[PDB]
Amino acid sequence: NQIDRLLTIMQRLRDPENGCPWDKEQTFATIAPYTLEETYEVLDAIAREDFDDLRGELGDLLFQVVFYAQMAQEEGRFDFNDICAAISDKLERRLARWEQIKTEERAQKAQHSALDDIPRSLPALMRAQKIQKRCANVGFDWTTLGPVVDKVYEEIDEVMYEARQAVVDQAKLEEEMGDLLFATVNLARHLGTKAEIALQKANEKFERRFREVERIVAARGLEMTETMEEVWQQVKRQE
Amino acid sequence: NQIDRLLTIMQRLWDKEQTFATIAPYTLEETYEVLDAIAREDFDDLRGELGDLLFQVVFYAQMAQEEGRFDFNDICAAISDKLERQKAQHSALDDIPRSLPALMRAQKIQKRCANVGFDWTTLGPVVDKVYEEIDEVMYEARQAVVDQAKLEEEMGDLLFATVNLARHLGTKAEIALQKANEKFERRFREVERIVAARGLEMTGVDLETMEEVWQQVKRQEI
Image (cartoon, rainbow over all chains, first blue to last red; front, top):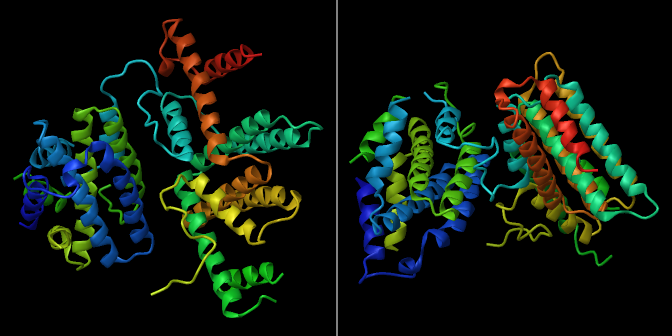
């Protein structure tokens, strides 16, 4: 029943008169980056496992979904109930998997490439892994794990060859670097992992350690008067 | 009132469960789908994607509810009430949005550390750290029982090491892989064309044939 409050508040926020913000001037395009922002906040409240945070952040994600439904309903396309109607239909007719729902979504109705309908917005690691699995799905993939590792080693040698040259060709060095990164995604994938998520967790790990070394060096403290690699070591230990 | 219906469908529906993950990666994947549908102004796609997104909000609410954490309507209450309405430690790492691509974000973090004196002075140990991470990853991979959490941890760290290499070599990792993604996709598309021109299905060609085409395509560039 609170959902119904949300819906009318959302209605009343765009009520034209009255209205508003601001809200009134938001479109599908202007809400988009907030949805991106908000989804990572959701994923962060999850990683940190706090549910005070998470219940707030899901509220904000919902607010998003309700915002899109309203803007769609204002053009007569659909409303919130039709969104809930269609997922409910799909989940009923099908628990899960989530892969299943997604792949039969795709099954309509390209035509042409393996390869088509890949969001142009995707972070590079997400996009490489998606390209690779699309190609795997049609049978283009390595069959064993070892040549995958070996392709990483080959691309490292390639990168390092370019880097060693008397005159470094920067474009060619960037190209090899790119193929090395692609190869490492192929390995991540062959290992059962998601490359973009894996690096997100390594980023938080490193950031958490660095922040601690900062806290330690700072508490020291004073010093206008290494240091650093040894504290990094200790913080690494205390973990 | 299909809102009530979806909810009760959640109470009642891989089919293991999971958990806050493996849902969370799905929240990220679906969010890009939603933004793409908005970018391509396709409102039929959009309706479906919002259903997919909504379904995860409901799932999160269901797990939360099972744990006694006040649930789908509190979510609604929370945001409604809100809509009717002390320093952290200082850091060189501040203002790097969570939502940047992971590679771009690793490279940004490493530069902040470099600014402040925390970086390798020579290329040798950067290279070493990559080869060492590949040992640690592959070590976890071939263990009789694979610790999945540790494998992913080491896979992450290898990715972070390879960004450090990219950076010390004067390159931006996220852009470099985008351009590798485009090269790969170009060439696979040619292989798709060549096979279609024989009137075959890609799913009806053996891997050896695929590889020989792939090689012809790559020989057709130089």
